Each structure stands twice: as C-alpha cells, then as structure tokens.
Amino acid sequence: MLVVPAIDLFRGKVARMIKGRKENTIFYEKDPVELVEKLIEEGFTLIHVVDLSNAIENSGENLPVLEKLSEFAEHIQIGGGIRSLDYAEKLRKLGYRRQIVSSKVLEDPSFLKSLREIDVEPVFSLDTRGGRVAFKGWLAEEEIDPVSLLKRLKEYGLEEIVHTEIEKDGTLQEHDFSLTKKIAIEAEVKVLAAGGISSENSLKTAQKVHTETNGLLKGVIVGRAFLEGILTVEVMKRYAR
Image 1 (cartoon, rainbow, N blue to C red):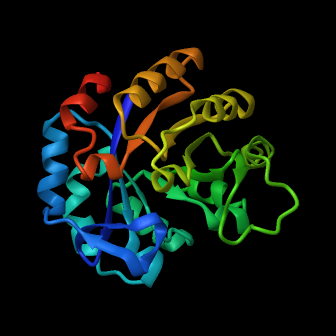
Image 2 (spheres, rainbow, N blue to C red; image 1 turned 135 degrees about the horizontal axis):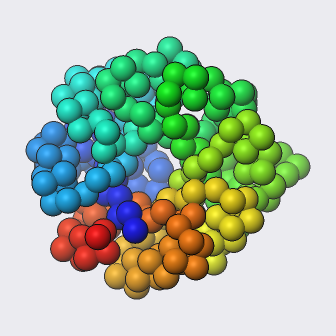
C-alpha cells in the first residue's frame, strides 16, 4: 500500500502546529527540498505537503519552495488554502496534479468539477471526530454523517479523499480503521487514512484493511510520527512496497 510522508510548510520552513493551534507553532531544522529529495530517493512515490502560509496567513511565502519542489510535483499532493480556480491552475502549472481541498468544496461543490476541467485530481480532506464530520465552518450543520456527506459529493465528481480522525494525534491514541473502512466501502471512495498513524501496528492494520477493501483504502499518511522519528523511514518503507 502507500505510506505517505507528510510535512507542513510555514514561512519557507518545515513546520508543525500542535493540535492545530497556530499559537503553538514549531519549526524543524530540515531543508524542505533536501527532505523531499531524500524521501524520493528512499522510494516514496507520494508525499503530502501543506502550505500553511497560504492556508493561515494568505501568504505566498512558500511559493519559491513549491517552485523548487515542482521537480517532484508528480509525487506530491499539495494542500493549503486552495479555494479558487486561479490558484489551482497555478499549482497545476507547477505540476501539482493532486490537490487537497476542503472548505471551498463544502461552500461550492461544483468546485470539484471545475478542478477536473483543468486536469486536477481534487482530493477532499474529510475531517472527523468520534465518527462525526468535524469542520470549523460546519459545526452547526444538521448532517454530520461522513458517508452521507461523501455520497452527496460523489454526485459532483468526488472520487478520492484523505480521511483524518482529527483528535488522535492529540489524545496520543492510534487510528480507528473500522471507521475508515466503513467510509471506504459504503461511500465507495479511495481513501488515505490520517491521524493517529504513529506505530507499526497501525501500519500493519492499514495493510489488512487495504486488502479487506480491495484497494479502496490506498494507504496512510504519516505526519507527526514521521517528523518526530516515532515511526522511522525504515519501518515506513517496510510497508511501502
């Protein structure tokens, strides 16, 4: 299956905001380009990159790094404030075909079709907690059943998502793959599992669910555990294949 290393970029540097809080931001002493280059060399074919400068500060400070990383764009799925077709087109020109989107799709689902018109694969970031859809701007919404939401978006062309159980990294618990499996099978969508991916058991389990779902669960995304060295590249590679 796929084992996708993930890194956040903020002001040109590899970063991480603890439990999604900007007031608690940390920077890793690792060059973003050398890091991605090493991952490509170690055999990883897909890397998850999030431009926090664009997402949080509406800043283009990370563009130069993303342009230097365009050399590996075919192996990168990029996210971070992608809310307009003009910006999606710019990233696609740089080679980023796989783009992570979320809030814009909830506001205007036709955005999905529009992205496909410029040959972008819109990967919807589905955030959940306790099995319920949990998005910053949709906390009062009547429907918060994951499968229900996805079925609605498939009518608009949705085919793949990143399913993140958002509280796992904070509660120091591992991913609950039963939910991911249910979403994959019932909504019939391709899924990359995220959140609580910090142990070999989680990788072992994901590989099993990868099989039980006949491939719908494409693999997992390793973020905090990857950058913190909790999950070594050796172990990650063992399940990459």
